[PDB]
Amino acid sequence: SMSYSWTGALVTPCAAEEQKLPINALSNSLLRHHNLVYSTTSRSACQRQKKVTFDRLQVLDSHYQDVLKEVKAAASKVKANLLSVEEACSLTPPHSAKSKFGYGAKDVRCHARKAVAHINSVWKDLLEDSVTPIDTTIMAKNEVFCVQPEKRKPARLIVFPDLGVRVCEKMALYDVVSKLPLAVMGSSYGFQYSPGQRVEFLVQAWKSKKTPMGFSYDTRCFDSTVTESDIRTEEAIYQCCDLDPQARVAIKSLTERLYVGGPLTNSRGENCGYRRCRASGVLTTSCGNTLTCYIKARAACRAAGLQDCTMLVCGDDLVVICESAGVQEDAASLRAFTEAMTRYSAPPGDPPQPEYDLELITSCSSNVSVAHDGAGKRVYYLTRDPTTPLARAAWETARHTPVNSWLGNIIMFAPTLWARMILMTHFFSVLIARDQLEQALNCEIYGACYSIEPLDLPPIIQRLHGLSAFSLHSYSPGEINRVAACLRKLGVPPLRAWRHRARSVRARLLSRGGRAAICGKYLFNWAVRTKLKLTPIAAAGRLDLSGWFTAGYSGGDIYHS
Ligand SMILES: CC[C@H](C)NC(=O)c1ccc(N2CCN(S(=O)(=O)c3ccc(OC(F)(F)F)cc3)[C@@H](C(=O)NCc3ccc(OC(F)(F)F)cc3)C2)nn1
Image (cartoon, rainbow, N blue to C red; front, top):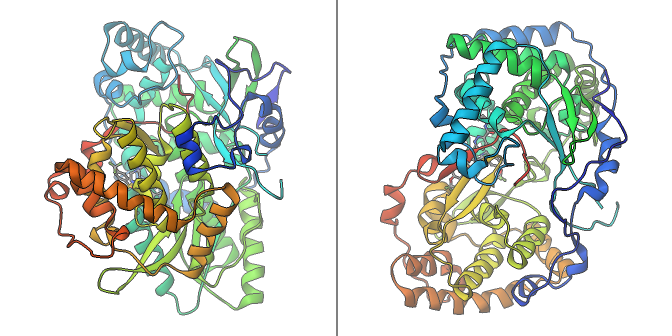
C-alpha cells in the first residue's frame, strides 16, 4: 500500500511562520551571517509530501520470523500497568497542541476538571469502539537550519491525534513503552544511556572486536517505511505483557483506529489525505520505531551473515559494530544487509558505508572524539558538527521559543569544545543581560521534556557527564577544525574572542555568589590561566537527574500550540 494518499488540500499553518532569522544585537553577537539561517515552514510541505509518499515492499523470511519469536518471548516477562488519568495528565508536555474540545496542555497538566472529564469520555469511547478511524491533524514542523552547499530542507510533517486521545495513549501504554524496549533488547536499547554511557558502549563494542568494522544505517523516511503489518506486530508484542484488562482493549482500539493509519485533516478542517504508515506524533512512535528497527536490523545482520554484531538502536537510528571479514567482503556483506533491510521495508536513504575508524561513524547525529582530562588521561566523548546547534541558538536568542534547543545542547554536549566556549559563554552573558539566571526553561531531548534552571547546570553536568566535563582539553585537530570552519561559515566570532568574553562572564557570575558563583567557577575554569580546584559539587549528589527535572514525554514530534 502507499504510505500516504493525498487530496490536493494543502498543509496549512495556524499562525504566521517566520522564514528568515530575525535580527537583534544579542543574536548577532553569536552569529552574523543571518541570511544563511532559515526556518522550515508550511510553504515547503508539498516538497516533503513527495519524498514521504511511496509504495512499500515487504517480504518476510525465516530470519525475520526467528527474531520476532525471540522478541515476543522476551516481552512475555514484562508486567505493565494502566496509568490513572492524573498520571497521564502530569506527563503531558507543556505547550503541546491544544484540544479542539475547549482545553489545552496547561489545563491537562493542572488536572483541570473540563480536561479530565473530556479525557474520560475519550477513554470510554476507546473501550466501546475498536474500529472507527480517529482523526489526525497534519502540520509542517518549523525547525531551524543553516543553508547547505549540495542541496534547503523541506519541513517535516507531523501527524497527531487530538490532545484528549494523546492523554489516553499514555493511560494505556506509557508503562508499556517505558519497560518493553529494555526487556526485549537489553544493552542494544539506546535510550537507557546518557552521552557518557553511549560513548562507553561504543568504545567497548569497538575494542571487543579483533578487527572492528562499523556502520550507521540510514533508512529512507523510516516512519513511511513502517507498514500496517509492522504496526499490528507491535500491537501483538505489547499484548505479550501481563496487562490490565482495559489496557488490552484500549491498546487494540488505538492500534486499529489510529496507529495503523487514518484520515489526515489540515489546520483549516480540510481533508488532506489518508495515512497507512507510522504517525510521527503518537506515543508509540519512538518505542515502535526502536522495536521495529531492532527486529529488522537483527534479522538483516543474520541474513547477511555479519559476524559478531553489536547493535545500538534509538528509534530509527541504527549503528552496527561487527567483526570485519576484509574490505571487499565487508562491502559485499553491507550490500546484502541493505538488501535484507529493503525486503523488510526499511530501504536505505544514503547507502551504508563500512567504517574502520570509530570516529568516522555518525549516529544520533554525533561521533566519538577524544580529549584529555585534568590529569592528562584520555577521555572519549560525543560531539557533532555545531552548525545546527549554533543556528538554532541564534534564533532562540532573537525570538522567545517554547522549547530551547540551546539548553538541551549544553546538557547533552557539555564536554564539547563548542558547547563550553560558545554556548555557555553566550547564554550566560544573555541571561545576565536579561536578568534571567533564575528562570526555569524547557528543553526536549528526544521527546523527554525537562524544566531546568540555568543555575542548576553545573550539578546536572557533573552528575550526567562527570567532573571531567569541566576540565577537558587537548581536543583533536579534526574537532578543532570542524568547529573553526563552522564559525567562519556562520560569521561566529573565533574561539579566542569567546575565551576573552568568558573571562568577563565568569567574573560577573563569581561576584553574584551562591549557585551563580558555582556556574562561574566550574563552567568557566577553561577560560582562566590560574585554575581553581574543582571539587565535587554537593548539589550534584543531592539531585536525581532522571526524576527531579522531568516535564513530560512525547513519543514523537507534536505541534507546539
Ligand atoms: C519511552 C520509551 C522510548 C523508546 N524512550 C524514549 O523515547 C526516550 C527519549 C529520551 C530519553 N532520555 C533519557 C536518557 N537520556 S540522558 O542523556 O541520560 C538524560 C537524562 C536526564 C537528563 O536530565 C536533565 F535534563 F535534567 F539533565 C538529561 C539527559 C536522554 C537520551 O535521549 N538518551 C539517549 C541518547 C544518548 C546520547 C545521544 O547522543 C548524543 F549525546 F550525541 F546526543 C543520543 C541519545 C533523554 N529516554 N527515553
